[PDB]
Length: 326
Ligand SMILES: COC(=O)[C@H](C)NC(=O)[C@H](C)NC(=O)[C@H](Cc1ccccc1)OP(=O)(O)[C@H](CC(C)C)NC(=O)[C@@H](NC(=O)[C@@H](NC(=O)CC(C)C)C(C)C)C(C)C
Image (cartoon, rainbow, N blue to C red; front, side, top):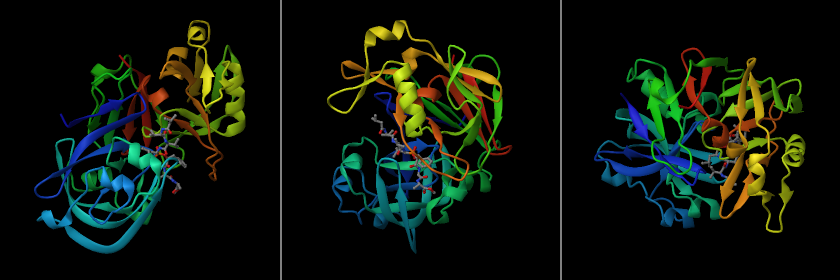
């Protein structure tokens, strides 16, 4: 029953409306499985990005509780500092009482200024949460507000309406077949093993396995810079004059699927998904980024992947469920 509709912005970002405070002040937030903190802009913020986004006003809420603690969060794209406070967060028809969240003080740079969302609602594990702030979903579960300690995500394609986050439930209308269950390797991000990445029965990357995260907040398929450089040559991407990694739109019809094998099951990504149409030209859905951790350099299975596969995030059993979208 507890669905939260998400707006699809150019197949790059997905965000939904939440209410904070009594009475509710409305904000748009990216529902991000790559991070664990909830924050919104506030009146304490004087950064450029704070001036053109909705700002939380503590004085207007009858249920706001202040702390003396701060938070500092750095993302791949964007960063914030803020102060932690407690209030009621309305999300997915759930009144999430006594929720700790960040009230931004600084949001430096161009990225957050141009972004259509106000904040981020992190959906990963408490262990990666800045200042050890209780994530939203952990607080919902701890208060017995859902019955099933899971949430599932359907992300629409080609700017269509219909993207949803389902709290404490699955909807089998969104997928075909049955869910394939994959164990989380490390409890931080929603981290899994990718057995191999193949094209025409040949391993193009991750020949003996690699570590990947299932990240709703990342647009593209990202990996370490050297394996990605190989994937770019394999799909005929050339580096254009303006910074982009471009492919001829004509070529989509002749390229093979890139197959991600996960727990001995094949998950093909077609060239109509991994080659993106952005602003007249066609671009590679692969991005080179080095994200070093103690399990290796991480791959990100971003929105390119998730659009193809309905994704269930099971906290009861520490597993990810995958099935092809209907
Ligand atoms: C504890 O460890 C850490 O603290 C490190 C410093 N940071 C993190 O873990 C933080 C919380 N998470 C993170 O930083 C993780 C990635 C990550 C995963 C493991 C280790 C390192 C990074 O990214 P998120 O998904 O939360 C973020 C959400 C955005 C802002 C809406 N997305 C990102 O920052 C990614 N940005 C995007 O994909 C943006 N789009 C693009 O840049 C694509 C462009 C339009 C071609 C978004 C507008 C969709 C980049 C990674 C490309």
